[PDB]
Image 1 (cartoon, each protein chain N blue to C red):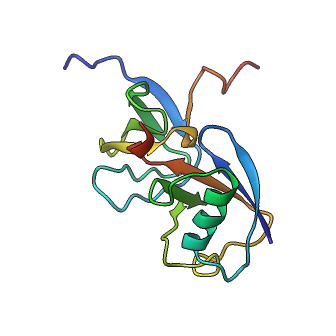
Image 2: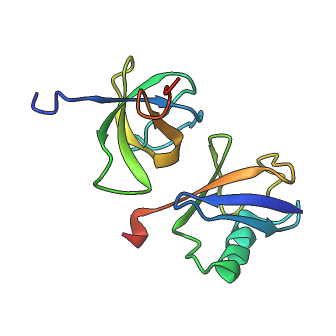
Length: 71
Length: 76
């Protein structure tokens, strides 16, 4: 695997995906940011546990360490 | 009523719409307000993606709530 740098984010909004290309993201779980610059509205996230990857809304995913903990 | 439809770009607009209005008509209101293609507009409330042919009531959306408006890759 070349995409071994999985940038970690946390899903805040509980979003149920109806399409397989979309990712069902359960509020409170962990997601890996695959691509976040290919598109602005929808990003590529992968569920840490489920291993499912798909498109999700940008402002539904909040990167860990980044702005989640400055305390 | 007034719903806070917050676009993914950060444009949070207060939309005056009827509780029994369709999401279709809501998109028309936004298309009047800001001017965005309805097909391109995906309204997400509490993680529930709203269909055009359904109303605010069909998804049980109370007034003065914040809906997230995520656009398709139609505008990109």
